[PDB]
Image (spheres, grey):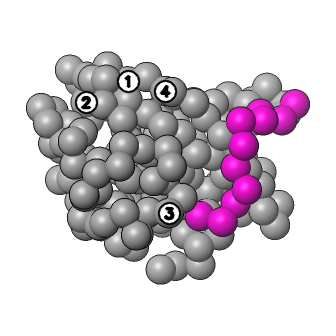
Amino acid sequence: SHPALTQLRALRYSKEIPALDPQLLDWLLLEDSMTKRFEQQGKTVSVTMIREGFVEQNEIPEELPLLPKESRYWLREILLSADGEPWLAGRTVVPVSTLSGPELALQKLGKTPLGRYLFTSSTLTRDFIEIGRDAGLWGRRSRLRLSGKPLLLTELFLPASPLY
């Protein structure tokens, strides 16, 4: 798709959280998407849609080991911009079994940027967070649960983002 997503997917992620500046840790560990924290930089946050749709297991080789094995997944790839400047690449993989209740909205976001602010009646927890780095750029990979139901979110922080 876009080279930022290719890069994102190929980061070598692990559960090692490096010994980083606390403010950088707070960015990487945030138990939410980056949308509202990027807005708090004094920015309007927008989505560039790279791909979204239902896919089979063969299009989620990175996420499949980390999710239930089932027939279909919602796959969403975006670039996230702040005042029009790309700051993040995001890749979300949602098993269809997660798409129930308020979490049906995960397939209906369109250009609305993901975040907990959209899920005002759903618990959010995180099963794990992995960190990776490539070419000087940080990425992270999380298995999230919304009302107990899993999804995979992988994010790559692009060079203009405030992490750097």
Q: Residues within 10 Å of mark 3 (few under 14, many from 20)?
A: few
In the image, 27 versus 150, the foreground residue is 150
Is residue 87 in view? no
Q: Is residue 12 inside the magenta stretch?
A: yes
- Image side of residue 135 versus residue 102, left or right: right
Residue 117 percent location from the top left of the image: 31, 31
- At x 66% / y 66%, what residue is drawn? 10
Residue 119: image tag: 2
Residue 23: image tag: none
Tell me, yes or no, whether the two marked residues, 1 and 2, touch with CB atoms within 8 Å.
yes
Instruction: Give, as a three-letter code, the residue at label 4.
Output: Arg
Disc 3 on helix, strand or loop? loop
Residue 124: image tag: 1
Residue 126: image tag: 4
Q: Earlier in the sequence, mark 1 or mark 2?
A: 2
Instruction: Give, as a three-letter code, the residue at label 3.
Output: Pro
